[PDB]
Length: 65
Image 1 (tube, rainbow, N blue to C red):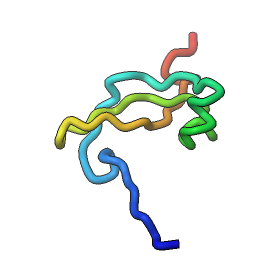
Image 2 (tube, rainbow, N blue to C red; image 1 turned 135 degrees about the horizontal axis):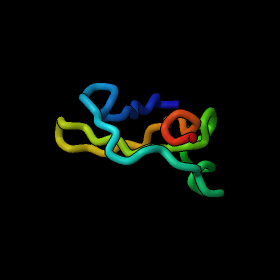
Image 3 (cartoon, helix red, strand yellow; image 1 turned 90 degrees about the vertical axis):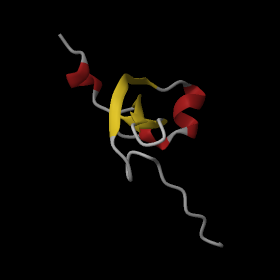
Image 4 (cartoon, rainbow, N blue to C red; image 1 turned 180 degrees about the vertical axis):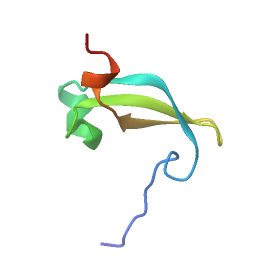
């Protein structure tokens, strides 16, 4: 309707994967869209204002023997 604008910090700031992405519970994924393609969401912090966002990463490459 109005056109609310909501964005992350990694899109406008430098982020650092501090916490690898992991599976999303029944509510974790149902609420987070990042759990759609990979289903695993990591925790990246932005050096700018130290902001931790919920991103999605590949687990098959992060840790797959």
